[PDB]
Image (spheres, rainbow, N blue to C red):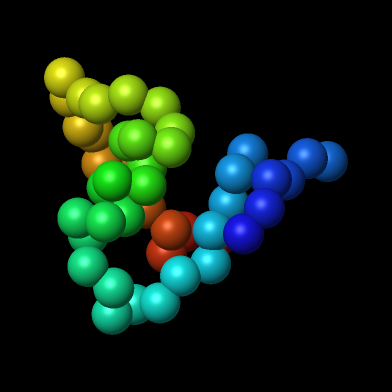
Length: 45
C-alpha cells in the first residue's frame, strides 16, 4: 500500500479479479470514465 512522493501506488497479484480492483479504483479514489485510452509502448528503451 501507500502514497508516493519524491501518487497512490499498489502492488498486487496477477490472479485477482478486475471488478473489485475497479471498486477500489472508482470508489475509494476518483470518478468513472466517458473514455479510456490505452497506449502500448515499453519495449522501446
